[PDB]
Length: 80
Length: 80
Length: 80
Length: 80
Ligand SMILES: [Co+2]
Ligand SMILES: [Co+2]
Ligand SMILES: [Co+2]
Ligand SMILES: [Co+2]
Ligand SMILES: [Co+2]
Ligand SMILES: [Co+2]
Ligand SMILES: [Co+2]
Ligand SMILES: [Co+2]
Image (tube, rainbow over all chains, first blue to last red; front, side, top):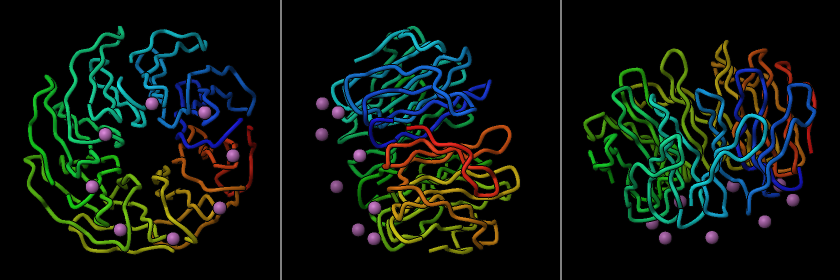
């Protein structure tokens, strides 16, 4: 990643690994080590992601928001 | 939220997302991104919440307390 | 507690809540909010506890050790 | 360990305890408190490890990488 990986990884139902970085992104990494997608927030993603029953990925950011990200890497919503 | 979301979200049995904020609050957010409730502690909620078998939400605060919050957002107890 | 509760709580099989504090202790709190026991390490317990299959509670400390604590609050071992 | 254990332990299917240290290593500790192996990254391992379905251990490092480590302590891959 572009900065410290302070965030703790979460593992999806299909093995996808999700983790934040101080480079401001939430990363979705395939089990083979190849990027699935990254999603840019406005600040360090120190928070560790959680995965909902429908696969939504939730994570906080130092930009003050809680993010809900769809499994395909598109924003679902953010809460300030 | 009002400050960095350092805390890592927890997901309840009904999909509710709980997370602390450096704005001093524990947040309960519905899966649709709308606030269910927030609970104010005396300092940053860096700690990440855990959910008990009866749904109680437990989280630490930089105000020195461990909080137990009922699912409706009312204080159950705090331990110094 | 005596200092910031940075650590994230873990919940045991019987509902006991375990959490570290920057006051250097690992706390075991009953679901009713009353202390079961506390265990003193040599520095802040920022690490969040994990519970093994036999109930052992594991947590790191800023004193450089990983601690294994028995369910009764007595040290099992520490690893430097 | 050689430095603060900020990381939060993860427990494997066989009881192995995995945790990072600010000494830059990911540690695998047997339930008896004896080292199984340690793996050196390039910076503090503040991130808390997660365990995949095949036992792979994933953890971030302040060296900017997400690491995937095999259960025997050998690198599987790292993602920058
Ligand atoms: Co750096
Ligand atoms: Co930045
Ligand atoms: Co801010
Ligand atoms: Co404040
Ligand atoms: Co204080
Ligand atoms: Co101290
Ligand atoms: Co030290
Ligand atoms: Co260093």
